[PDB]
Amino acid sequence: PSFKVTLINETEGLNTTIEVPDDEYILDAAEEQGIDLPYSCRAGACSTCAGKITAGTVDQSDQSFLDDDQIQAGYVLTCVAYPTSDCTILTHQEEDLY
Ligand code: FES
Image 1 (tube, helix red, strand yellow):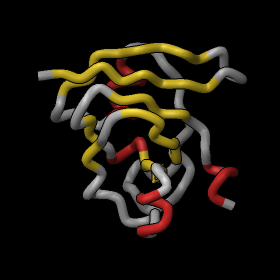
Image 2 (cartoon, helix red, strand yellow; image 1 turned 180 degrees about the vertical axis):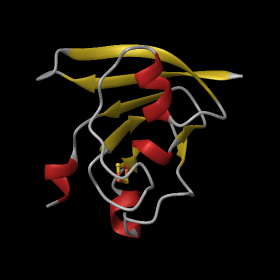
Image 3 (cartoon, protein in one colour; image 1 turned 90 degrees about the horizontal axis):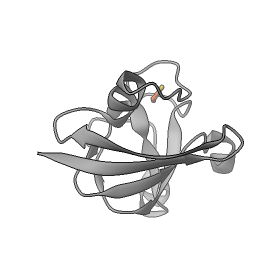
Image 4 (cartoon, helix red, strand yellow; image 1 turned 30 degrees about the horizontal axis):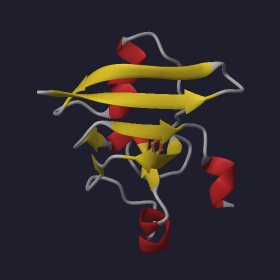
């Protein structure tokens, strides 16, 4: 099973919905389909790949940087996030965490 993940960053000209297997991280699946997303550690330990969820849900249990307030506010570490429903994610949201 796969989910439709809408990735959005209009300064990049990015507004694209891709099919992501339920066992693949969003960053990896995006890259495979030719999308460029920001990243550094790829380990869920920083905020470089941070995005913000505006629709749908993810499993990011592997992440270890975002606190509970930040998770509640919709933030996601795309390098370690599986989609769990069709979802919409604003990418390059690191500065919004400041
Ligand atoms: S690139 Fe460091 S948490 Fe995703």
